[PDB]
Length: 338
Image 1: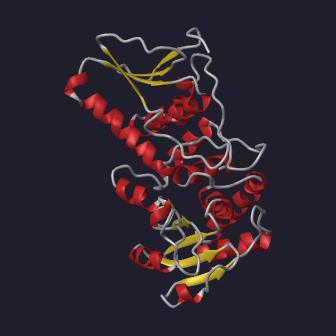
Image 2: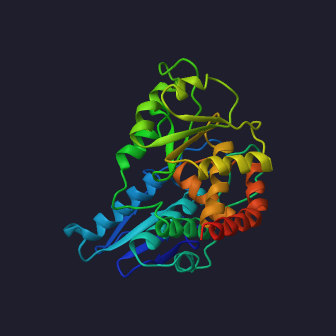
């Protein structure tokens, strides 16, 4: 809460990251810009980040354009963020993602550069009520982004921004791809659509066309029955009911059946719960931990970058606990196929 706390961190010889607690003092060869009021996190409760894939893409495009433009040719580009620690965390997340994706930096090097001026960052909270039981750091987020690049989850050369931004909106279905051509996480459909007057309650029908055009062969419901499974199976989708209470953790039987269905699925799997966040994210996270050997923290971070608010409360603890078992089952899966 004073200009003594201001820190300037050089990213490249042209790009700089600044955390400012006062008036951004200009210079003739310095260009200041902030994303604090442009790329804002849409919170559910006390969760403040990380920002989604679209915002990471928009930021990366914004810096790439700024470093390319004739207007700022010999100018130092300074990304500044304000006094709010929540905004500082998100801004640093964006810089570190940029370092991992568009520069050849390792996650640890990106994190080293960001914490350089004894800079302390608050780790990301979950969407739960009250107190948080597990936090994801910036390093967890960078490790998630790097592994996403290596395993093909993130590809900014073929990323469709318009499609992501259209389908994430509650009015168009509240859908997000976690793993391209393999996993969709979405909001639970109701019997009868109610898309008018502030309501964004979709019926199974508004997903059918998108699903069949993007090779979804399987649909898994973890929610209580709000629609008849026929409305999906009549369209040739393999529908599975794998129920577990709202806000609960799944049993070994539900996790194993989820994995079996997903492993034996021919095309993409579309998973939903009420909001498509808690129960959905937890199970998709179990698959990612098993088949890609990613940590609970890295996995939660990735699912949250693709779909904010995913994995809530007790579910974070579950994934942290199940990490070793999922890793062992994944080692045994790959040796059985070899």
